[PDB]
Length: 477
Ligand SMILES: Nc1ncnc2c1ncn2[C@@H]1O[C@H](COP(=O)(O)OP(=O)(O)O)[C@@H](O)[C@H]1O
Ligand SMILES: O=S(=O)(O)C[C@H](O)CN1CCN(CCO)CC1
Ligand SMILES: OC[C@H]1O[C@H](O)[C@H](O)[C@@H](O)[C@@H]1O
Image 1: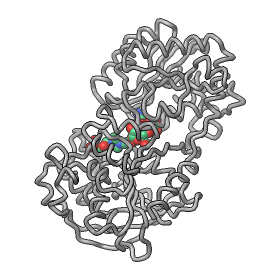
Image 2: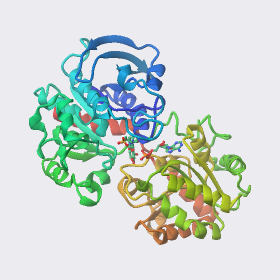
Image 3: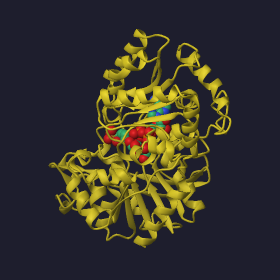
Image 4: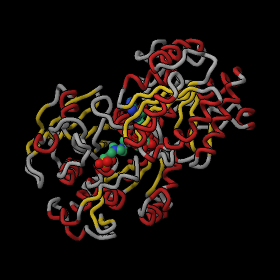
């Protein structure tokens, strides 16, 4: 069984969010579980420099110009790179320029990603050919389309990590991407009078996967599908939609071995976490105080994440005696709002705007609560990281958060199953109730400790996830 993942990022080489974490860990899990998994990525500078043993497999001409297909290894997994410097050798973000504008040739940059994914099924590499092309998110959405147009020389799975990113391009670009014009149809890749790469992935794949069981159910609803629900309802009825929960990479997210921490610790030695908290407070400019709960955010700052609710809830949180440490980058309204909060409440609110990989570990390892009040959340990896680090997740019951966190209710505490704090509605009052719940449990230190140890007993394993994908791949044949 040979599988090629087609995607635009991979931890630790290039990361803008959880997708990178997935691609960095799943393939090695699949190999352990008996599937020859390989990865296809554009040769962005950071990726190209990480894969030091990469060799030439072939040169091709393409609707988007020439590629050199490279193959090397990273952390033992086979990595193909699309070297096309005219498309991919640009600084910063893979998706947009310095001014945060999408590249004007994005249609070509990502149509090419899908195209190479599909070519691989036809022998682009004379030495290896995937049985299944596994495409991730809109960026790779054309791969099942090129496969369909070639008579499906391999099976395809499409996994949605986030349905809110649709890969919308003007219809005239059908001219530029070498797909049958007949594909521009509602029974095809057309969506609201434009090309959608997301629609393409959803429509042409043999099977669609979402990144949690409940997100898979949610995307059949208008509220979470944004127009795509009709397609998704049909694919569900056909038995072509399913949810496979993400795992966590233990090599990197384990307080037991985390080299980025002031102090390592375990489920049975949580007293060793205290030093991380002290150093976090010092680093953030917070009052150094072990009697007070430290709430935390590590997050992209977009409306998905419900962090406007945190801004609203903040006075209530501070009034009860809590602290907030935030790390994040995104909407300037959010950035400025949180910066204003830190200025207004020095020693109670610490804020760091930007992307800081190492600093997220020090927050995860020092904080008491991780706020994930998402409006929607396909999976959420930060709350899984919180569980593992005994930093109790406070979450909205939506998507993967609904699948992974158990509220501190009477039954859950009595059944020994409670692991965090759950609220229902996307408003600050509903959030503030879960926050109050946290303060109440905080006032009972041995119950807090009991919930911490249950959080740390939760297991999110890539090799277990691998087993589900494997069933899928064999089912498709
Ligand atoms: N500002 C940041 N600095 C460092 N890491 C971040 C930052 N924002 C998000 N992350 C990381 O990116 C990943 C986010 O994944 P996830 O919670 O699945 O949400 P999303 O993929 O929607 O961003 C986590 O590993 C998280 O720690
Ligand atoms: O905004 S774009 O559509 O131009 C590019 C991406 O969709 C932005 N991302 C990166 C991939 N994503 C998953 C990150 O884990 C969603 C946000
Ligand atoms: O699948 C990895 C990640 O994909 C997307 O970025 C989602 O926004 C996030 O919830 C998920 O954890």
